[PDB]
Each structure stands twice: as structure tokens, then as C-alpha cells.
Amino acid sequence: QSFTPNPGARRIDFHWLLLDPNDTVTFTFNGAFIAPDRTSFFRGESLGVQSDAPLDSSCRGDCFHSGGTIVSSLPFQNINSRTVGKCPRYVKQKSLLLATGMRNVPEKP
Amino acid sequence: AGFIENGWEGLINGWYGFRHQNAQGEGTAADYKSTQSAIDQITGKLNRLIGKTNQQFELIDNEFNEIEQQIGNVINWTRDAMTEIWSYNAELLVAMENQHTIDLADSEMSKLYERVKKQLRENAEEDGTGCFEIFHKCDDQCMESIRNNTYDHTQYRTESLQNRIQID
Amino acid sequence: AGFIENGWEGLINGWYGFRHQNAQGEGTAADYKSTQSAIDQITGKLNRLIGKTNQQFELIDNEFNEIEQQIGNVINWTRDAMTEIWSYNAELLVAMENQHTIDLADSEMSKLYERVKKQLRENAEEDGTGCFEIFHKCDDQCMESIRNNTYDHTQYRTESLQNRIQID
Amino acid sequence: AGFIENGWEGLINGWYGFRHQNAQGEGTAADYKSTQSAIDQITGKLNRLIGKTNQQFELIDNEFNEIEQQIGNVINWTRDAMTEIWSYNAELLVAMENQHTIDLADSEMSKLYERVKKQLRENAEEDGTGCFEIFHKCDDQCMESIRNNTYDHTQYRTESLQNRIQID
Amino acid sequence: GDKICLGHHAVANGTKVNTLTERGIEVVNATETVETTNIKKICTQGKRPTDLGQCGLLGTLIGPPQCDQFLEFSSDLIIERREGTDICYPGRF
Ligand SMILES: *[C@@H]1O[C@H](CO)[C@@H](O)[C@H](O)[C@H]1NC(C)=O
Ligand SMILES: *[C@@H]1O[C@H](CO)[C@@H](O)[C@H](O)[C@H]1NC(C)=O
Ligand SMILES: *[C@@H]1O[C@H](CO)[C@@H](O)[C@H](O)[C@H]1NC(C)=O
Ligand SMILES: *[C@@H]1O[C@H](CO)[C@@H](O)[C@H](O)[C@H]1NC(C)=O
Ligand SMILES: *[C@@H]1O[C@H](CO)[C@@H](O)[C@H](O)[C@H]1NC(C)=O
């Protein structure tokens, strides 16, 4: 890819590349090039959550969302349509009651 | 002098406890194995649902910033449409599980009617409300016999013949 | 001399009308309550479907103009895929409702076979085609008895014994 | 001296072959029509599934090149989400077909229990494991009678009365 | 004289469910499959998160002054916040 700066507004445009092992990244500079001093390597599958909630050192859970966390043993949630990590599905049905027994044939005749 | 019918009773002794209307004034519950059979299947329903929903998710939308609105409209539309698809699937699946749970409850009770009928053959008259009218001196021992599956018309029919037989 | 069988009859008097083959030449229909029970559930099937489809929609595509083709291809693909998903859901759901409707019809008729069997006990021989052979003088009054649930082997069995009994 | 029970037998002679435990040492299979009825429905299950999946597809993604990543992320997300939707639909549909196949197998066998019961009326005692205890000299001819639907208590009951009757 | 009556564990008025036949059928015993409990704090029982605060995620590759301490890190969880930014001097990726 080739690039050229366009004068008329102060801005730094960052561009990125994932360089394969044993390959060589070649750069050609004619100016307006902000060079990296260091590169980056990835280590161990993080979960990038975007949220306003405070941290808690006793709380444990997999589901994170902008308003907090979802800790449950249930397949569905009504809390947020945007979740991170392994989670229950978002539905518009605020109350999906699943019977765990027989119907209530009324106690009084 | 209650007209004993389906043992609604406000029963606390098991989900499928059956009332034994002993003339001596008893109300003992059924063999736990019937209830246990229901428990063995129903309690696992939650886990079956979990395995169908517990998936890895990642952020597509940058909530604290802005994405090109034309794409964002496609994503919002897509997510909303998928939400309705999954909501439909969820309602349908839950409804299926609820209907199946009811069907199971009716099926298990049906099996219990069969247990009485196949063992007594003639002296078990079904009232359609869960009740069998028994034509012999069916005291607590017969309840034990039912629960222990020693209930058998080979002897019990004769005991009822003393109370029911008509020869003509 | 028809071989009276399942009362197909080109019947107009209710969905679940039953033919009473009175030797005197009658063809009166069944208690409307059986038909009504079917009506009470089947007529509501449409409304159950409506509640699952009646949703607010807005235009995404500007039909009289043009949207970037790359996005338009995604939208068309998405809509088409969703159309197949909803078409699948629609066919499946309708098929489920159709199968359930058939199952309901068979279940209700099954209950009506039971109504006859439980009340007559011995003189109701099922032909497997909806017909019961009755072993007593079952004139219009017995049809009224069935519809009024006064049909009872306590008296009717004896009436049949006059026509059926064998002592040995 | 085997305790002949449900004819698991490692049977090769048809899916729904029934063991006839002739005291003379026979193990002949059932009327093929029962098996054929299962075949007529089950073999078509694959075709029913095919009609719901066989659709025209085109390339959206240029696999050997690159598409704008933002759109590609939407497409990959959409396809993956749809894959889960279709995988869910596939698992559910297959599970429904499997449950229905099992229900069909139980239903057909249930009909075969009924065939024996309705024809013999009193001398067919069900063991709950597919076995009927027969109270008469039921040699190969009775098996032919069952398969030819000439099995009839009108004559067979009398044959059993010679072996079973109690007068009191 | 004696009866066997199959009970349905019919407790005092309970809750209702939606089925394939009717909606709002009252049942003795049920559980909700949709939880609405929103825990307003972030769980950290694992490799504790990089709480970027004023730092944005991309900032960790660039090094705004608020990101200087987060230039090299490891965790099973990364937290971004509304006040966070990836730049000090205007820019985009
Ligand atoms: C990287 O290049 C070196 C050159 O000496 C080679 O030995 C090594 O195996 C290469 N690694 C891979 C993954 O090819
Ligand atoms: C997408 O939906 C969110 C709410 O879930 C809304 O804030 C956002 O503006 C929507 N995007 C567009 C482009 O309308
Ligand atoms: C999308 O489908 C419509 C017809 O429904 C067609 O007219 C339109 O050109 C399609 N869009 C693209 C980009 O092909
Ligand atoms: C989309 O998925 C394919 C693999 O199916 C992957 O190679 C491609 O890079 C993905 N597209 C993007 C933008 O990540
Ligand atoms: C019904 O289920 C709930 C589920 O949380 C349980 O707490 C309750 O005790 C059950 N009711 C009984 C067993 O009467």
C-alpha cells in the first residue's frame, strides 16, 4: 500500500499490518512517517469489555456488558443486547417462564 | 365428609404424591419413584436450554463512540431481526418445553393409572379425576402393596369378591 | 341397505357431528359441545399466529433510488436469507399447527369413543371407523341419553342382556 | 429354557419382526406389512429434509482477495449468526424427526399390540415388553392367522376355554 | 370404601406460563429462564483486568501519557471507559 499526507488539517493517521513469521515488512520513507520503535505480540485470549461499572475483587462471572455483569445459570437474559464472553441469548421476551412441574389444577373447587 | 377427588390437597409431599383415602382417615403420599422419574427429566431441561445458548460473543458496535450510520443501521436492523428470530425461537422452544412438560406430567400420571389397572384388573374404577374407587378393604397395607408392587389381583380380587361378587 | 360406516355423509350439521344409525331411519348429528370444543381452540389459531408476526417495519432500501451496491447486496442477501428463515419458520409453524389440529381432531374423537365406552362398558363394539355396534334397542332416546350424559350401563346393560346374555 | 421377552434376538428379518415363541421351537418374523408401513414413512424423511435445504447460493465473499474489513466483519458475523440459526434449526429439526421416528416406532408397535388384543379379546396378556402370553395351542398356524388377519376369538377363545375356563 | 386419588401438588395460587396450546396457563412450579439481575460491578476473579481509565485500548499501542503504564500488559479481561481516549493529538486508525 502507498500513502500520502493531505495538508489542511492536523491529524495523525495510524495504519496497521499483521506480519507473518519469517516475513519481512519493508518500509519506504519520504517524510511524514511516524515510525514505531517497538512492535506487538499477543498473549492469551483477553476479553475487551467496554463498560462504566467499577471493579470488584470478589465478583466472578463470564458475561460483561456496559452496565455491569450477568451472573446466572440461565439460557436467556433481558439485560443487554451487547455482551462479551460466553453468554445467554438476548430476547425481547422479558419473562420466559419455564414450567418445572405440573399445571396448577386449582386447589379449590 | 369430603368428596375425595383429585388429591390437590395443597400437597407438600412430592410433586406426584397420591392421596390414599383410607377409611381410617389417612392421606399418605405416593411412591417417590414416580416423582423422581419426573425430577430426573424436568430438572435437566434447564441444562438442555443452556447448551443451545452459551456461545462466545464479541463487541461489533463501539458503544462509547460512533460507527458509520449506514452500516450501523444495517447492524441494528440485523441484530433486531435476529433478536426477533431468537425471541421467536426462545418462545417457541420454551413453549415446546412447557407443552412437553405438561404432556410428561399427563403421561406419567397415565402410567400410574395403568399401574393400578394392570395389577387389580377389575376393582379399579377410574373417576377421570385421578381417583380409583377400590372395591375391597384397602387399608394402609394396600398402599404399601402398591408402592412395593406386590399389589396383585390374584389375591386382591378374591378379597373384593367377598364384597362385590354376583353370581347369575 | 347401506353398510353404515364412518359418518362422512357429506355432513353439514357441525364439524364433529356423529351419525346415529337408528333402525327407524335416522341420521341426527352429535352433541354440539364436541364441535364447540374444537371451535374454541381452532378458531383462535389464527390469532396465535398473528401475535407472532404483527411487528413494526420501516424502509431500509430506497426503492425509487439507489444505495451503494455493496451494502445493497448485503441487505438483499440478509433479507433473502431472513426470508428463507421466516419462510422455514412459517412452513414449520403452520405444519406444526396443522399436525396439532389433526392430532386434536383425532384426540377429540378419541374422547368421544371413550364417552361411549365408559358409559356402556360392554355393549359398545368399536369398528375402528368411528362406529360402535350397539347391542340393545338404541332408538332416538339413547341418542338423547348420550348427548345428555344419562347414558348408563346400570340400566342399558340390562336392556342388552335381554338381547345378548349367555349363561354357562 | 430362555425366558422369552422382547424379541431383540439380533433379528435380521425386518425392522419390526416379531418373535413367535412356538413351543415346538420356532422364531419366525412378523408380517412384513408392519415393517413396510415404517419404511414407507421413514425412508422419505431424508427427502423431506432435502426440500428444505436445497437452495441456490452465490459467492458474496471474494475468498482469494479482500473486501473492506468493516463490511467483511458484518458479513462474517451475519453468516456465523445465520450458521448458528441454521445449526439450531438443523439440530432441532433432526431432533424432532428423531423423536417423531421413535414415537412412530412406539405407535406402530402399539397398533400391533392392538391387533392382537382386538382379535383375541381375552387370551392376550401383555407383559409390557412386547410379549403376549397366549392361553391356547398357538402353533405356527396361529402365526399365519395373525399375519393373515384370520385370528379371531370367535374360534380361538373356545380353543382357550378348553385350557382356561373356570365356571363358578 | 377406599380411594386412590392422583394428586397434582396444587399449591395456593402460583404463576402462569405460555404454551403451544394456550397462553397464561397457571402452573404449580416453574422457573424464569430470563434473568434481569444486573450486577453493577465488574467481576475480576481471574487475571485482573487492565482498567484503562482515561487510556483507550488502541492507546496501549501508541502511548498517550495516560497510557504510559499500560504499554505492556497481560490479562483475561480489558476494560474501556467513556472518558478514555487513544490520542492526545488528533488522529484515527
Ligand atoms: C525463519 O527464517 C529462518 C532463517 O534461518 C529459518 O531457519 C526458520 O525456520 C524460519 N521460520 C519459519 C517458521 O519458517
Ligand atoms: C443502533 O442502536 C443503538 C441502540 O441499541 C443506537 O444508540 C444507535 O444510534 C443505533 N445506530 C444507528 C446508526 O442508528
Ligand atoms: C436488491 O433487490 C432489489 C429487488 O428486491 C433489486 O432491485 C436491487 O438492485 C438489489 N440491489 C442490488 C445492489 O443488487
Ligand atoms: C471473514 O471470515 C474468513 C474466514 O471464513 C476470514 O478469512 C476473513 O478475514 C474474515 N473477514 C474479516 C474482515 O475478518
Ligand atoms: C417450585 O420451584 C421453585 C424453583 O425455584 C422451588 O423454589 C419451589 O420450592 C418449588 N415448589 C415446591 C417444591 O412446592
Image (tube, coloured by chain):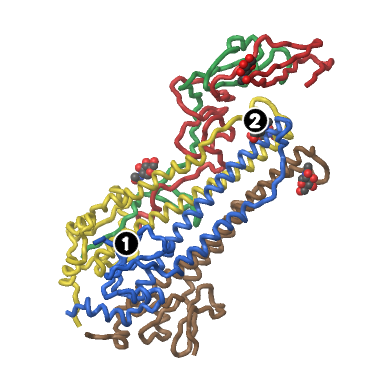
Chain colours: A red, B yellow, C brown, D blue, E green
Quadrant location, ligand no. 5: top left
Instruction: Assess disc 2: are there few (<14), some (14-19) or many (≥20) residues with their C-alpha within 10 Å of its C-alpha.
Output: few
Residue D133: % across, % down: 28, 68
Q: Which residue is mark 1?
A: D128
Q: Which residue is mark 2?
A: B61
Q: Quadrant of the N terminus of chain D?
A: bottom left
Residue D149: % across, % down: 40, 77
Are the residues flagged by discs 1 and 2 from a single subunit?
A: no
Residue A56: % across, % down: 47, 21
Vertical position of residue B63 compared to residue B111: above or below: above
Say which of D8 and B120 sits in front: D8
Say which of E90 and C156 sits in front: E90
> Which amino acid, mark 1?
Gly
Label 1: state its secondary structure: loop
- In screen coordinates, is C40 left or right of B43? right
Name the chain under label 1.
D
Say which of D145 and A18 sits in front: D145
